């Protein structure tokens, strides 16, 4: 119940959660591990980790290249779970969620994929290409292995979707700021959806997509969300400093400090 | 949903939550259109007076001399655009218009779906956005130019392996943020429901015409209908009206490339593994890790790294049979039809002919009434076969 | 002869004495065949089940919006081979077979007649000999290869200007010493009798189908039928069934090239001088001395340096009207049909469309029912127009 | 009546006529004039002259190139008639026949073309591409200007053609040795046709096509023909010695001497 505790703790502090996203193994395994520790050290409340896929159809150019860089480095799903185990061995309480594509979890059995998550210490899993309509087996497998199935609540959702997401989801509800794909390039009135989700006893909502400025996370918290997820803004810093790993870390630090402070 | 998204284990709607309303919308538009005599006559009119429907059924006599095989060819090479792909896009374009949409998004590898999507839009006043992997753009100058001359915007995709795979990716990416005004014209009988069902339904003419045609010319249904399988649209269009006719064999032919053994093929239904991709549960060109692989074939049009769910299903229950043909084999059938029949077949269709040619040659004394779907023209491949 | 070799002053049989029996033979074979219900059904069967007959008549709505012109297009681009030339060679090949002949001799410039002659022979078991001027052979790699792949022997003619002109020469040269076993498949409605009459008769479907088609769709005959004129076969095929319909205008369009004024054109019927050549008395691309000149045009298929005698005759009596269209004009009509109708027209046919487009544009308020003969597909010209 | 006299004279000598063919202006006007004089000096009884055409459809490769060479030299029909006048001014009795294509004679009026022939002193004209069926205007124009219309009698001719050729023709009947085009490359039983033509009071028959050896002309005479026409064998000598005009003449001389002697 890693998310349960983080949110309860954050509430006692009347605080919002800042959750950055990165691709495991970008730009290299060793540098990626280093990035994640910097992310945690600078203040990230939880983590959203993506394992390299050949067809990230819900991702914009920034993360598309994160996958390309990770691939260019020879990172595999096996290598990722190895990475996840070390991260958990290092950081005991920080919630860990995986951004996954369907084939990677269906490949060697759905059940077997979630058992691995439990073994490694993963907390949640969001399968970008599985709608609620198609989530039955993923949900079931997740719950069975004490993994929280993360559901995306889009901005256009009707009452039926909302009631579904609230009932099935766990850990946190992924509130979609926008339509389209993952991108800091474009920004994104979630008041009604957040009240409705709170009304249906849904998991605390985390707003994701386009969140790239300190003001954006404070706005997320003010509306009633428990926090904000930011990815392309982080990945863009890795992209920016490929020739200077040390500079990468220091810049990653300043950004997530600015971002976490804005949720307090 | 109003219809079943699955064919047994196969199919589904594996798309991000955001595209679900766009898929339910499309489905209702289809169920309505399907029951609409006014849509039906509009589509039949375009197929007939614009496309060339009904296409011919040609008895190939010279080719089967000295054997007990009577072979016919469903002439989809005579359809406007030079391929069966035209039937489809016309009906999908009218569906977009029925939906009040005025924009079309398209996916293309060889260039054929793009050219057909572009022509349909030009005719129906739709604005066309087409996505092609950079490797294919460079590889297909003629079709790119044909597309542009038809008023379509061609966009190269440098992401991933820059082919059909990644093109299909940029299409959905775009569609997630534009489904409200744009319709994504998927190019085959695969992808998320309602596409495998829509494409079949809009390609059904083929088999329906063939049945009437063979019943006229021979007073009998065929022993077997054969068609190549890239993603499954021309094949399923041939099969459809004959599925309930249990005495008629349904044979789908997948590219074998350099040889199945070489691992250099495009035969997922038979030699690939089931996975989940492109909003579908279906057999796939996959790595051991679950990473999506590319399909290989002498014919660029059979490069879809997966296959339609209805085929995977028909295969599983034994209703349909799937086989594969290598490059040299397709090259041979290509060469043969040119010289004995005077018809230049697409290398795509040549895989289908090659199998019927085998069925004949291996058993010349077997009485057999065959119908091969010549899904397309081969002028396109004169250069390739030349080199 | 059994039939009149002349159309007023035009036509004739200007061949060396040696080829006369070969022309009288052919004529009797034609008069017999023409009266033969068994030949008639054999030809109708091939046209239908092999070629794609009947071709469509497409109403071009987007193209004529904002004017009082209703335009239709006789879709000869949808015929097997991609041009009206196929109708012809099929009937001429059966005539060769009726004559006990088992060999075909052919003449070709752009490559289109060669490809059609080659396909007909492949289908009908005739041995095909094709003659092409070296300049055209180098210029037409795709069609040469298409011809060879169809089992035809391609022979380059380095004599003279090495084009259609000299090819037509080597054909007759060969035919003089082989008419006993070989039939010379002339590619247009010109040359010595009985060819202008045979080609018309075997291209008549076009106009006959159009009449029935327009009477169905509009309940009225057109105000005018338009067709390009290279040698005159597609045009005459369109005109034929409408000649006795005096209310229907017959408009033939000749290439204007860079401009008539430039002397860089292929418009003999209107801007050339009557002479005697290729076994015919007809208007000609001639020098002041009487030396035969070459016809110029952006479209290689309209390079015949002369024109059919029936056209010259219809022109003289006022029954038909002939005009010309320049390269840029044809290029414009080509571009326009691609974008507003989604049809890629042959540059040959683009000359015909361009004129109908003028008839519209110059007088947008004139009520007009037009039918353009789209004698062919334009995939062939994608490269030319591109550069 | 130049042909009338030559044949009457040749008969009193129980001799056959040897008639060579050449293209006017091949390889040049001046060299061509020189060739023709050599032809006459070595023994030719009559001449068959071709004026350069762009489409000689009844000619094989040898003469095709004669036209090409003449064209390359800038020879025109006007230049030809000029050449013909000088030849007649030089040689008063030798019969002169023109090998013509239809367009060249129809160009500036058929009548006007034959008046020019009469003016220049031409004796006969054979229009290679005009059959008897189409010769009415050419025949009429020729007779009107005292020019003999030459008709080709093919080896396959039926009684009706034979009777036609005999009635219309004048000067000499062109007996076709073979089918096909003009060529020394291939050779070619004209007994019945020659008796029939003699039976119908036809003009003396001259055998043409493939005649390239001394034995061939003696054979022509033995069968009942009044002579033989030879072209490609002559033109081949011009073709052979383009780089040696002097050698050309001496070789042209030896050939026509051998050929004329064989008719005696
Ligand atoms: N990658 C991804 C794709 C689909 C659904 C959720 C995620 S995880 C968070 C992504 C945030 C990226 P960005 O801040 O640029 O919008
Ligand atoms: N040139 C020509 C063409 C048609 C009819 C007569 C002639 S004149 C004599 C030609 C002799 C040429 P060859 O001896 O090679 O057969
Ligand atoms: C487009 C294309 C194909 C691939 O076809 P599917 O029918 O969807 O499998 C096959 N044949 C031709 C000629 C094509 O152009
Ligand atoms: C062959 C060719 C022509 C020239 O035609 P004629 O009809 O004999 O004048 C015209 N259009 C096309 C498409 C051709 O291929
Ligand atoms: Na496939
Ligand atoms: Na012309």
Image: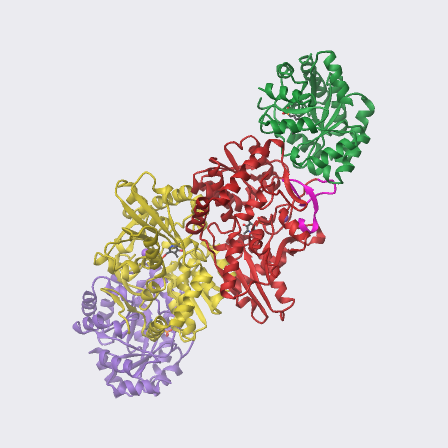
Chain colours: A purple, B yellow, C red, D green
Q: Is B255 located above or below residue D160 in the figure?
A: below
Front residue of B352 and C241: C241
* Residue B174 visible here: no
- The N terminus of chain A is located in which quarter? bottom left
Q: List x then y, in percent, for residue C76.
A: 51, 54
Q: Residue at x 53, y 31 (%)?
A: C178
Q: Where's ligand 2: which quadrant?
A: top right
- Residue D56's place in the image compared with A16, above or below, is above
Q: Is residue A101 magenta?
A: no
Please provide the residue range marked out in magenta: C268-290
Q: Is residue C17 left or right of residue A81?
A: right
Q: Residue at x 46, y 55 (%)?
A: C54
Of residues D106 and D88, which is closer to you in this image?
A: D106
Q: Please identify the quadrant where the C terminus of chain A is shown.
A: bottom left
Q: Position of residue C252 (x, y in %)?
A: 62, 55
Image height check: is C102 above or below A143? above
Q: Residue furthest right?
A: D89
Q: Is residue C284 magenta?
A: yes
Q: Is residue A189 left or right of residue C66?
A: left
| Observer-nearest of D100 and D10 | D10
Q: Quadrant of residue D151?
A: top right
Foreground pick, A126 / B168: B168
Residue B39 shows up from this direction = yes
Looking at the picture, how far across and down is residue D165, in whole percent?
66, 28
């Amino acid at each position: 119940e890693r998310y349960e505790n983080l949110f309860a703790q954050l509430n006692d502090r009347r605080e919002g959660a800042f959750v950055p996203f990165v691709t495991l193994g970008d730009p290299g395994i060793e540098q990626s591990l280093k990035i994640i520790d910097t992310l945690i050290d600078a203040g990230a409340d939880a983590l959203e980790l993506g394992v390299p896929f050949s067809d990230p159809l819900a991702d914009g150019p920034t993360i598309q290249n994160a996958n390309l860089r990770a691939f260019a480095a020879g990172v595999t799903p096996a290598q990722c779970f190895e990475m996840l185990a070390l991260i958990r061995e290092k950081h005991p309480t920080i919630p860990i969620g995986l951004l996954m594509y369907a084939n990677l979890v269906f490949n060697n059995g759905i059940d077997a994929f979630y058992a691995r998550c439990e073994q490694v210490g993963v907390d949640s899993v969001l399968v970008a290409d599985v709608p609620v309509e198609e989530s039955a087996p993923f949900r079931q497998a997740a719950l069975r292995h004490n993994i929280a199935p993360i559901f995306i609540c889009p901005p256009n959702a009707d009452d039926d979707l909302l009631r579904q997401v609230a009932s099935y989801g766990r850990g946190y509800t992924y509130l979609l700021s926008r339509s389209g794909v993952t991108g800091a390039e474009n920004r994104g009135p979630l008041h009604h959806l957040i009240e409705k989700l709170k009304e249906y006893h849904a998991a605390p909502a985390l707003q994701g997509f386009g969140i790239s400025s300190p003001e954006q996370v404070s706005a997320a918290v003010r509306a009633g969300a428990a926090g904000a997820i930011s990815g392309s803004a982080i990945v863009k810093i890795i992209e920016k400093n490929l020739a200077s790993p040390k500079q990468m870390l220091a810049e990653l630090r300043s950004f997530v400090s600015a971002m976490k402070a804005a949720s307090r | 949903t109003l219809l079943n998204p699955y064919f047994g284990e196969f199919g589904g709607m594996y798309v991000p939550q955001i595209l679900m309303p766009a898929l339910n919308q499309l489905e209702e538009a289809f169920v309505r259109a399907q029951k609409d005599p006014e849509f039906q006559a509009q589509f039949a009119d375009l197929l007939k007076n614009y496309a060339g429907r009904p296409t011919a059924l040609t008895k190939c006599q010279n080719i089967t001399a000295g054997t007990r095989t009577t072979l016919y060819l469903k002439r989809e090479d005579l359809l406007h655009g030079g391929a069966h792909k035209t039937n489809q896009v016309l009906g999908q374009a009218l569906l977009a218009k029925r939906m009040g949409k005025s924009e079309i998004i398209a996916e293309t590898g060889a260039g054929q779906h793009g050219v057909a999507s572009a022509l349909a839009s030009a005719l129906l006043g739709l604005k066309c956005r087409i996505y092609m992997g950079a490797k294919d753009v460079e590889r297909q100058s003629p079709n790119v130019f044909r597309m542009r001359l038809m008023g379509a915007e061609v966009i190269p995709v440098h992401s991933g392996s820059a082919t059909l795979k990644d093109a299909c990716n940029e299409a959905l990416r775009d569609w997630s943020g534009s489904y409200e005004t744009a319709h994504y014209m998927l190019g085959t009988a695969a992808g998320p429901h309602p596409y495998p069902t829509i494409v079949r339904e809009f390609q059904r003419m083929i088999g329906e015409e063939t049945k009437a045609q063979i019943l006229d010319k021979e007073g009998r249904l065929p022993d077997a209908v054969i068609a190549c399988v890239g993603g499954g649209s021309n094949a399923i269009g041939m099969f459809a009206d004959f599925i309930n006719d249990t005495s008629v064999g349904l044979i789908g032919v997948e590219p074998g490339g350099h040889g199945i053994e070489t691992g250099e093929h495009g035969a997922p239904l038979k030699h690939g593994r089931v996975g989940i991709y492109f909003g579908m549960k279906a057999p796939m060109m996959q790595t051991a890790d679950g990473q999506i692989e590319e399909s290989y074939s002498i014919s660029a049009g059979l490069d879809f790294p997966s296959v339609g769910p209805q085929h995977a299903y028909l295969n599983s229950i034994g209703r349909a049979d799937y086989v594969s043909i290598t490059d040299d084999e397709a090259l041979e059938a290509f060469k043969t039809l040119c010289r004995h029949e005077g018809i230049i077949p697409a290398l795509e269709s040549s895989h289908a002919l090659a199998h019927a040619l085998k069925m004949m040659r291996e058993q010349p004394e077997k009485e057999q009434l065959l119908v091969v779907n010549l899904s397309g023209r081969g002028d396109k491949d004169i250069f390739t076969v030349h080199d």
